[PDB]
Image (cartoon, rainbow, N blue to C red):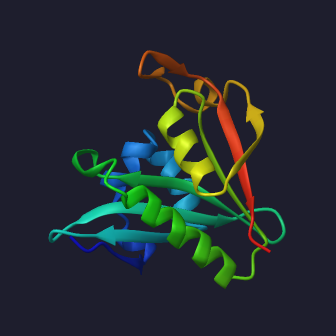
Amino acid sequence: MSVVIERIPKEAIPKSLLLLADPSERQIATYVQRGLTYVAKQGGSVIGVYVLLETRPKTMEIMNIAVAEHLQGKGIGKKLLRHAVETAKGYGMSKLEVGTGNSSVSQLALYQKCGFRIFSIDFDYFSKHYEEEIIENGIVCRDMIRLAMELN
């Protein structure tokens, strides 16, 4: 029942779960080396993850956030997100960012419910970063929608 979230070293990342949110192992490598990875545990296993990266001044971005497929829509995304926000304040950041695909409409609702505001679109992001096309609920995942939150 109880989800426990903790830091892990980069040598122990769940590539497995990170690949759910980000199909390329080379992409994942780009930000795990430089960033901070936290995992969610429950039922005797790692079932959630997020990676924070420090980007522009006083800014972190959630580079990857993932929940085990069979456990999605149970409030675990909510929980990881709350934790990312708190971790980011802790580090003295004033801005938290997260990107998601145009097709990721359920994530778009989640992020906004949690305080993120949509501010920008990176066009053709996915076509450019991945050899293979991504389709999600009938919609081509083509562009990265950019969202941000002021922490203070």
Residue 128 placement: quadrant: top right
Judge from the rendering whether residue 138 lies leftward or rightward of residue 147; answer left or right. left
Q: Position of residue 58 (x, y in %)?
A: 80, 72
Judge from the rendering whether residue 43 lies leftward or rightward of residue 10; answer left or right. left
Q: Relative to 103, is 46 above or below?
A: below
Judge from the rendering whether residue 15 lies leftward or rightward of residue 54; answer left or right. left
Res. 36 visible in picture: no
Res. 71 visible in picture: yes
Q: Position of residue 19 (x, y in %)?
A: 38, 46
Name of the residue lying farthest toward the left: 44
Q: Position of residue 118 (x, y in %)?
A: 73, 42
Q: Position of residue 129 (x, y in %)?
A: 59, 33
Q: Residue at x 60, y 23 (%)?
A: 142
Which residue is at the front of the view, 118 or 144? Answer: 118
Which residue is at the front of the view, 4 or 65? Answer: 4
Q: Residue at x 38, y 69 (%)?
A: 39
Q: Residue at x 44, y 44 (%)?
A: 21
Q: Quadrant of the N terminus?
A: bottom left
